[PDB]
Image (cartoon, rainbow over all chains, first blue to last red; front, side, top):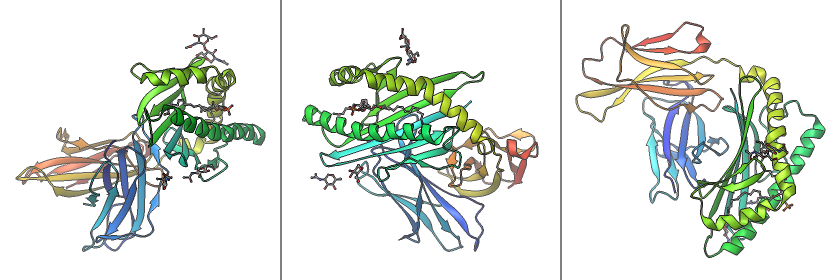
Length: 95
Length: 273
Ligand SMILES: CCCCCCCC/C=C\CCCCCCCC(=O)OC[C@H](COP(=O)(O)O)OC(=O)CCCCCCC/C=C\CCCCCCCC
Ligand SMILES: *[C@@H]1O[C@H](CO)[C@@H](O[C@@H]2O[C@H](CO)[C@@H](O)[C@H](O)[C@H]2NC(C)=O)[C@H](O)[C@H]1NC(C)=O
Ligand SMILES: *[C@@H]1O[C@H](CO)[C@@H](O)[C@H](O)[C@H]1NC(C)=O
Ligand SMILES: *[C@@H]1O[C@H](CO)[C@@H](O)[C@H](O)[C@H]1NC(C)=O
């Protein structure tokens, strides 16, 4: 068993009111069965796109999630992951 | 130059649930996917068939369709025998391909991990357990080695088919493999884990190919505090990377982030904090 690492980052420089893409890159996990949710103010974003599951030289899995978003001043965004290596879902916030 | 890898991911949860999913990469570009759900292998590029005819592709795919079914059966039968010694859940990964070298040279490989750990490779004319692999694998591998038609097919795929297929992909996928996309950079800050400090972040996004240079600078002086993170994929086959610099309050003034990339043709990006 290997615990996932989660990194959250935007595709373009963030500008308030302008359409962008938010990425959630989940790596270093095993086994490959995993649940990824992207959150807007703590609510699940419904249209999240997922890359195919892949793995590295070191055998650990990675997968990219992404969604359209348009950041504002007052919106918080996160990526939350459920995996058998953690008793608790891990949440990483966009900075 | 380029590494070609076919990645197989097989999961067995019980006697009646398994799935096998594959992806194929040429360098960092995905060329194929083969979901458990689908009978046929899917191209993820216009050129994913390389320079093989429709007939040669069909043969190749037909062989893999037979393999996928045989692989699943054989593993289930293996678990039925090993149990309770080894049981569910079971994870097997295969990584097979070749690496292309300068003057037309080629090296092939085929590796197998069980439960996330490297255990078996194909090498030369036969399969072998790697040193330190569990000993209960010696018998099944001997049994698999007695199947000489399988051994011949694997040798043919690694020795001949792999490099032949790849030269075709390299030629057919030329404009994609040699594409140049430009980094766009921006600066932000986040709290530091150290007091009296703030962490400055230089984000660099949308570049291709991978190699890139990013440094925080004070005039001509490189800031040795610069901490490059990993390469992170964008969803559009471009790359993302950030470089951070923890700064004391008031050393912030006069910092710049400088970015070099082959797509800029000598014209570095320089942002000032
Ligand atoms: C996508 C286009 C790229 C084309 C270029 C090719 C580059 C090479 C890439 C992949 C080549 C390697 C993949 C292997 C291909 C298999 C070839 C083949 O035809 O084998 C089919 C045969 C025929 O089966 P049958 O019905 O019994 O006659 O199937 C088999 O041999 C059975 C499958 C076994 C092969 C893999 C075994 C893995 C080895 C050890 C497994 C680990 C043990 C875990 C123990 C379980 C716990 C109880
Ligand atoms: C595939 O290539 C390998 C060479 O890497 C061949 O296996 C070698 O050749 C002979 C077997 O006749 C042995 O004496 C060597 O020890 C083998 N090398 C290794 C590293 O094991 C193999 O014969 C080739 N097969 C085909 C069909 O071309
Ligand atoms: C087998 O595994 C699948 C996947 O976890 C599960 O949904 C199913 O209920 C299991 N069935 C049995 C009989 O154990
Ligand atoms: C994977 O594919 C096989 C063969 O078509 C199928 O029988 C099996 O149900 C699939 N596994 C899952 C979990 O859907």
